[PDB]
Structures are given as structure tokens and as C-alpha cells.
Image (cartoon, grey):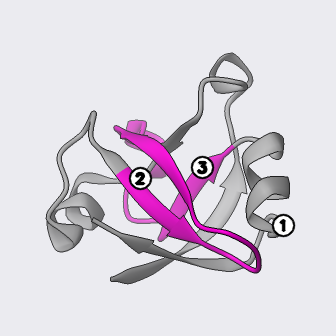
Amino acid sequence: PMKLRVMEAYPEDVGKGIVRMDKASREKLGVSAGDLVEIKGSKTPMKLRVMEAYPEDVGKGIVRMDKASREKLGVSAGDLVEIKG
């Protein structure tokens, strides 16, 4: 597993149940873009669909997810979350 820093979703991604993280991160987790990933925060795990990072977000150590997803997980922007592939 790996940990990444929660950040806000881009507006058009809100409500799609996706997370964006970079390709190095996906490679470390052994996941492919378009797969479900399991994320853990303070409550129950959640599965979210992992999608590509935008160029400007590469290397930032972040995972973008929307507010509904952060609330279900029990996390806020800036928190580490654990991802499993």
C-alpha cells in the first residue's frame, strides 16, 4: 500500500467517484488507470476509480477526490490516505 495527500477534485470530476493520481503512484500500487482502488481514511474503506493525473499534478504526491468521497472516507484536504491496489 501507499499513502498520498488528499486534494480537491477538479470541478468536472465531482460526483464521478474517481480519484486522480500520477502514473508512478499507480505503478507502485500495481494498478492501471481505469481500475478500482481501495482507499482507507477514518471510516469504512471506499473503492474509487483511479484515473490519470493532469500534467501539472505529476510528482506532487497527491490524490484528487471530491467532497462526497472525502466525507465518506472521513478525511479532509491535506490528510494522508492509504491506497491499496
Q: Earlier in the sequence, mark 1 or mark 2?
A: 2
Note whether 52 is above or below 84 in the view shown: above
Identify residue type, mark 2: Met
Which residue is tagged 1?
76
Quarter of the N terminus within the rendering: bottom left
Identify residue type, mark 1: Ser
Q: In which quarter of the image is residue 40?
A: bottom right
Which residue is tagged 2?
21
Residue 8 within the segment the image draws in magenta: no
Q: Quadrant of residue 63?
A: bottom right
Real-space Cα separation, disc 2 to disc 3, in angstroms: 7 Å
- Rate crowding at label 3 as few (under 14), some (14 to 19) or many (20 or more) other CA atoms within 10 Å: many
Mark 3, secondary structure of its residue: strand
Residue 20: % across, % down: 47, 44
Residue 69: % across, % down: 73, 48
Pointers 2 and 3 in contact (C-beta within 8 Å): yes
Label number found at residue 51 = none
Residue 2: % across, % down: 37, 82
Pointers 3 and 1 in contact (C-beta within 8 Å): no
Residue interval drawn in magenta: 37-65
Note whether 63 is above or below 13 in the view shown: below
Real-space Cα separation, disc 3 to disc 1, in angstroms: 11 Å
